[PDB]
Image (cartoon, rainbow, N blue to C red; front, top):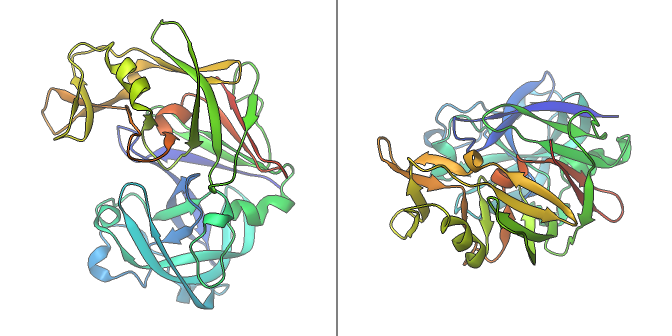
Length: 330
């Protein structure tokens, strides 16, 4: 089997991407944030504290003839950005782009933090990291991909995120029309539960490539590119007037600037992030200070190849017995 679904930016800055997901019988379609940095499929629901729901579409398990309470199971998750959610668990039928999993754990939120409430466009998350990170207790549950894997034509999914435009998540096949040149595959460590890999270096604009190992994670659920302070300083030094602002929370730059590109290495291959992808617009409405899309990972504890990086590539998440990651230009 295969599946193919369009993923759409939630706003004009590509702050996140949403993908429609069918849950239950008859189908209830919710727009979920596909997150290769976590491993829970959770949704706003009829059980979510009413004051914490503001415009989201909810899953109502009592209206699904295939929903079953997973007795005694609870979940609770906290994300890198400080947001969180928790609740109980149902199993139900879940379909993405024509690919159907029966008995998928659907984690129903009883509580969500303010950032989730305040984002009316995201109805929940669909985790695509390794199932070892799943938070369901006392019986850990499998991701949608893990459940689908054996049925797929090939044990892979691909992320093809757009810049200020829709893109695609495919399951079970590689669309050879969706990228240019070849896909370069690179080793993955699953030791931390992530799609963790090692970039071979970087360049800023038209500058020379610096060969240096950068361990980090391919994370579709993180907006920005978080890299070591040395790398980030080298990038922003090429933008007149750019500075790190403790008050704002990262590097900012004059909105009048033209940003240089940023290249990262994948083995001997190179992925080029155009300068415009690194512009996250005014820090507040009407400001001429703009927020940067490349930020320091110092004190995160891990480097994160988030959407800024991934949307410059066609990315293969290869879930073979020994997983790997593939990157192509597009």
